Amino acid sequence: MFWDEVYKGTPPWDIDHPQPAFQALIESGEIRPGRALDIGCGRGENAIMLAKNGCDVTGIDLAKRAISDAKAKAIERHVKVNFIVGNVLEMDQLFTEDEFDIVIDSGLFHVITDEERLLFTRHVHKVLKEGGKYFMLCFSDKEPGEYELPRRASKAEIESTFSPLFNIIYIKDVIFDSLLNPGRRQAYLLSATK
Ligand SMILES: Nc1ncnc2c1ncn2[C@@H]1O[C@H](CSCC[C@H](N)C(=O)O)[C@@H](O)[C@H]1O
Ligand SMILES: [Ca+2]
Ligand SMILES: [Ca+2]
Ligand SMILES: [Cl-]
Ligand SMILES: [Cl-]
Ligand SMILES: [Cl-]
Ligand SMILES: [Cl-]
Ligand SMILES: [Cl-]
Ligand SMILES: [Cl-]
Ligand SMILES: [Cl-]
Ligand SMILES: [Cl-]
C-alpha cells in the first residue's frame, strides 16, 4: 500500500537520529521513565532514544518495511523495543485502555486526514494513562488561509483538535530536522495531558 511505497528508499523525514525536539524533552526532564508508545514510529530513531533513556517503548507503524528496519536497528544498538505493524486508528484491538505514560507523535498527526482526525484523537486518548503525556511534533502554519501544500498545523488547528480530550500545556516553536534542502523546518511541539 501507500506507506510501503514511501519506505522503498529514504523519505524526507527518515533522518538518521532522533528528532531534536524529542531529544530536548529528555534533556528538560519532561519525558520521565515509564511506558511509552511512538505512534507512526517509522524506522525507530525516536523510539530507540526513549528506550535508551529508561522507558519501556512500543512503536507502531503501518509499514512493515519501516518496522522491520526499526527492529534491526534496535537489535544492532542492543536495545529492547516492542516494534509492531499496526494501524493507530485501530489500536484499541492492540492495546487496552489507560496503558501508556507517554505517547510521542513525530509527524503522524501531520499525515492523518481530516475525516480521521476525531477518531485519531479518541484512540490516542484511550490508550494513555490517567496523567499521561502526549507530545506531538508537526510543521507550523502561521500563514493566513489554507492554500499551503503539504498541510501545516496552526496553533488554532492544534488547539481545536486536541482541547476536547486533552489539557494543552504548551505549543512551542521548535525545529524539525529533514532530509530536504531546508534541513531545518519551522515546527510546533505540543505538550498535552490526558
Ligand atoms: N494510520 C496509521 N497507523 C500507524 N502508522 C501510520 C498511520 N498512518 C501513517 N503512519 C505512519 O506514520 C509515519 C509518518 S512519517 C514519521 C515517521 C517517524 N515518526 C519519524 O519521525 O521518522 C509513517 O512511518 C507512516 O507509515
Ligand atoms: Ca494556513
Ligand atoms: Ca493549516
Ligand atoms: Cl537528536
Ligand atoms: Cl490497517
Ligand atoms: Cl475498527
Ligand atoms: Cl496491553
Ligand atoms: Cl468515517
Ligand atoms: Cl483557504
Ligand atoms: Cl538533518
Ligand atoms: Cl481525561
Image (spheres, rainbow, N blue to C red):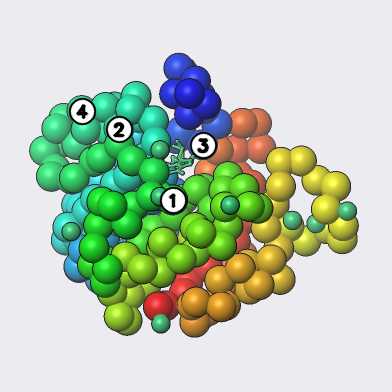
Q: Which mark is residue 13?
A: 3
| Sequence order check, earlier mark of 3 and 4 | 3
Pointer 1: what residue?
A: 89
| Sequence order check, earlier mark of 4 and 1 | 4
The one of 78 and 111 positioned closer to us in this rendering:
111
The three-letter amino acid code for the residue at tag 1 is: Leu
Q: Is mark 2 within 8 Å of ligand 1?
A: no
Q: Which x, y percent locates residue 151?
A: 71, 47
* Mark 2: secondary structure: helix
Pointer 4: what residue?
A: 72
**Residue at 56% over, 71% down:** 162
Nearer the viewer's eye, disc 2 or disc 1? Answer: 1
Nearer the viewer's eye, disc 4 or disc 1? Answer: 1
Marks 4 and 1, how far apart in space?
A: 25 Å
Marks 2 and 1, how far apart in space?
A: 17 Å
Marks 3 and 2, how far apart in space?
A: 15 Å
